[PDB]
Image (cartoon, rainbow, N blue to C red; front, side, top):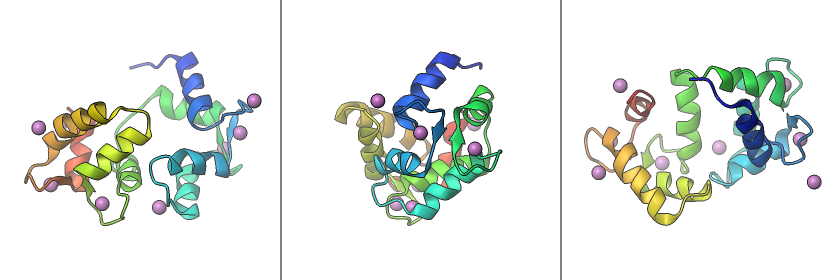
Length: 144
Ligand SMILES: [Sr+2]
Ligand SMILES: [Sr+2]
Ligand SMILES: [Sr+2]
Ligand SMILES: [Sr+2]
Ligand SMILES: [Sr+2]
Ligand SMILES: [Sr+2]
Ligand SMILES: [Sr+2]
Ligand SMILES: [Sr+2]
């Protein structure tokens, strides 16, 4: 569906551009990802910016880039993999229940809200019940 542009802006400010200058520069994207992957590498942060940076100015611009990306959200494996990798705190190519719960708490959920999100919705994709998601399990969460 179509997002509320005013909410997109409030989200962009609160997550990526605290100063509302219209750009999310390196240290801003890093402070964003560090909330939930505290030992995120500088190169991960750079690749996140590059997928969004259509004008090549090394920054995520609210306009046109954030609005373009968010106005028409769509599924791709590459896009799903980016969030998978950011939740894979130990980079072992699985997201465990505990990693997903810690990320949920880090982005502002209470302990019980985080547990109920992960143990309900996320683990519904755990086809072999081993307590963790592969990329192939995780990607199914985009098409309930
Ligand atoms: Sr200020
Ligand atoms: Sr900024
Ligand atoms: Sr990283
Ligand atoms: Sr840009
Ligand atoms: Sr992991
Ligand atoms: Sr369950
Ligand atoms: Sr599994
Ligand atoms: Sr589906």
